[PDB]
Length: 52
Length: 52
Length: 259
Length: 262
Ligand SMILES: C[S@@+](CC[C@H](N)C(=O)[O-])C[C@H]1O[C@@H](n2cnc3c(N)ncnc32)[C@H](O)[C@@H]1O
Ligand SMILES: C[S@@+](CC[C@H](N)C(=O)[O-])C[C@H]1O[C@@H](n2cnc3c(N)ncnc32)[C@H](O)[C@@H]1O
Image (tube, rainbow over all chains, first blue to last red; front, top):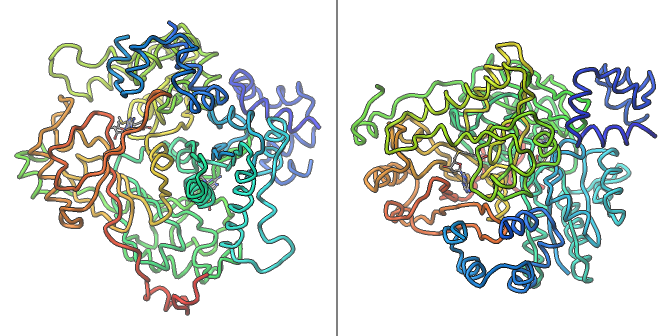
């Protein structure tokens, strides 16, 4: 799904990284991440992300 | 221009790097290096290379 | 055939060097040891011909000496080289830092008459300096494997930044478990107390592997290490306990002083 | 404005991380400190808005504390940030390893309320492990600045691989010169002789900066160091003088002996 695609892009694209750091939630929503996925990111739950 | 362009490509392109490793002189000749440039490379004289 | 060992760094996708990425792209086959499924997917998109070295770790609660895992990894890599493949080994971090498989594979490949080289990558300690804002040159740096520090005679310089790698398996002598015990960590604490007070602040550090993830930078007194939650990826940072003192003998020979 | 400090590694073009290259590409302005004209040209093609930090070094035979150069470099970087620029500093190697300009700029930027961060890069030490086929973990690793080793009481563990950085200015206290003298290096030799025999093989290492260039890997006895040709880029590797020996004290506490080690 979209998690892997998003994380790969974010990891190597400095423009996206800067956008993300300005507004994490908005950038994640713009890339289609679910509320559950966003919650896992914001609470720093890496195990949950892996399962999703 | 040409010397610099060659080194920049060689430095980041693993295909060209492996081609170069197999036959340094042929690859350098094909990318337009002069005999004097090739000599500097083979003798490991970085100072002369820079002058060129 | 030929061998190139590259590092992928610690962060997903972006921390590999440009040239190292190119090596992976152009490889006939890639042997991987990566942090997680996200990095695994990234790799497979770059080059689909991947063999995951993870398979060589103990699989189903088996008792297996880690040395045997490593030997099997090396043999897998060499089999590809021997067969004639342009082989790349892609390890997380720097492929030659606290990592024996690449060094071993390169040694063996050369011995067998094959071209073999290592490309440097960004290691866990490289990440630590950036994340903690510490220069290793400030008062110096020392690194040891934690178990090696326990089993062999090593003396740290307590004016430096000291890194104990593989802290999660400190003192685990069999090489057959992925964690140690609180009792072993207590012995390490007592050992370190030769140079570091029990209340000395230490840092459990984990570099992030994902772009949305913050590093772990957990400060605690040394005394509390045995109760701490440690992961395979944890590195222990022990900052200096002692300020630099003047080397008067050498200063005098140089003809200079503190001023 | 904002600040990101990135490393370009040691080799031209290919040793920068993918993300770090992207930072340079998208920067409003780039402050550079690179090894040579080839890397300088490479950078300019990535992003034409470059300010070369090399300008802040003493140009003439003028005497200038390197600490002053560093201050001016940091000020130039911060001036861009303060003005509102998305600023990137591109330093060779790792921007935070045996380097103060990035750490200083980041500290100052944060204090003034600007976003500032450092991206790790590939350092000279990283290159050494690869080029020499040595793992820092094999018997441990210690790194010191050569002059600091001389001026202050550092105590090496001779089972480790020991790196002395900035060996070419070992003992040069003024920070106004590009190199030291034989005399200073002889003092260092005598100091090291506490732990290392005079005939102990040491290695002068220089990582290559160009793809057509081999590293310098010069093996010589410690005694011969003062006659060696050293460059600003030289790092001295002092391999172990002693093999690892068992820590019977700790083995006893663990309730085991050598034979029990997997
Ligand atoms: C087999 S070594 C791998 C080192 C790897 N080659 C590198 O370049 O960092 C495993 C040890 O590296 C360190 N390490 C690995 N991943 C780490 C991370 N994300 N953060 C901190 N230290 C890490 C820990 O000390 C861990 O026990
Ligand atoms: C001011 S420090 C810069 C280090 C740089 N930030 C890095 O990551 O390697 C300069 C010292 O780094 C080391 N160094 C720099 N370039 C090197 C090279 N090409 N080969 C070996 N060591 C090098 C030497 O010890 C030199 O005196």
